[PDB]
Amino acid sequence: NGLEDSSTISFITWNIDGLDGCNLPERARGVCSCLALYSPDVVFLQEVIPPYCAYLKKRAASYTIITGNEEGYFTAILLKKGRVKFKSQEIIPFPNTKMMRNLLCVNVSLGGNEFCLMTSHLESTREHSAERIRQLKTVLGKMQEAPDSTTVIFAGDTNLRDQEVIKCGGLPDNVFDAWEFLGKPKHCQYTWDTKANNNLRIPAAYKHRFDRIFFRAEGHLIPQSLDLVGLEKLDCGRFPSDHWGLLCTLNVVL
DNA sequence: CCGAATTCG
Ligand SMILES: [Mg+2]
């Protein structure tokens, strides 16, 4: 990362399925190999568990780890040492969650710009749609409340179905979805796909765009690319996770 | 963490 690339922020968002204990150390090594290949400035993770934090300290040692809770399973935001300056951590509760979900925010400086970086793992399954929608509203509200000077990026596992975003009030006028902004490219549309991914051993073919990136911006933040990661089977014959990860690059413009 | 079917409280 040199002078030429200094206007850009790169990141990965990935639900890494720490609730699956089987082959977890090898799968963590697979996630870390991906981080080494692309060297993102920031990593947003969901379903981290305490042992997984130890694997990241060993095989992703160039990242500072900020977590959404201490026990059970939780989200994390990883910041590249020497690139990102950590300013503060905020956690916003979801009072009606039945799955210990919340909103994790980290305020940082990167590339001479101020950012509020946010992640969450919204309430899972079709049955919990009403609570998922209430949580999405909490997230969007927090994005809007940020100081006008700051660049806000949310990346996480939303568990959203398209019909649910419409029920919420659509994305607000100054908030954009990176995949939509880039023209809805087919190569990275689905992030959870049981035809292509065997980790859950589901004997059926369903696919969803559960993992999403929202940003608040006029002309000041411009997505450059979006691609999937984690599509290679590991030595054990399984993937790093039941989800694919997303690799995104954005340009910060005067 | 799908969704249809089933069983539990
Ligand atoms: Mg999961």
Image (tube, rainbow, N blue to C red):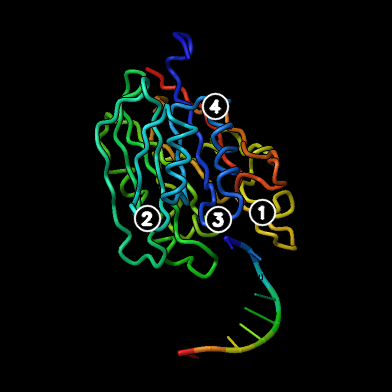
Q: Earlier in the sequence, mark 1 or mark 4?
A: 4
Query: Can you identify the residue that label 1 sits on?
Result: A199
- Inter-mark Cα distance, 1 to 4: 23 Å
Q: Earlier in the sequence, mark 1 or mark 3?
A: 3
Q: Earlier in the sequence, mark 1 or mark 2?
A: 2
- Inter-mark Cα distance, 1 to 3: 12 Å
Q: Are marks 3 and 2 in contact (CB under 8 Å)?
A: no
Cβ of mark 4 under 8 A from ligand 1: no
Query: Can you identify the residue that label 4 sits on?
Result: A36
Question: Under tag 3, what secondary structure?
Answer: loop
Query: Can you identify the residue that label 2 sits on?
Result: A137
User: Is A140 or A93 nearer to us in this picture?
Assistant: A93
Q: Are marks 1 and 3 in contact (CB under 8 Å)?
A: no
- Tell me how many marks there are: 4
Q: Residues within 10 Å of mark 2 (few under 14, many from 20)?
A: some
Chain of the residue that carries numbered disc 4 in the rendered image = A
Q: Amino acid at mark 4?
A: Ala
Question: Under tag 4, what secondary structure?
Answer: helix
User: Is A99 or A140 nearer to us in this picture?
Assistant: A99
Number of the label disc, if any, that sits on residue A21? 3
- Inter-mark Cα distance, 2 to 4: 35 Å
Q: Are marks 4 and 3 in contact (CB under 8 Å)?
A: no
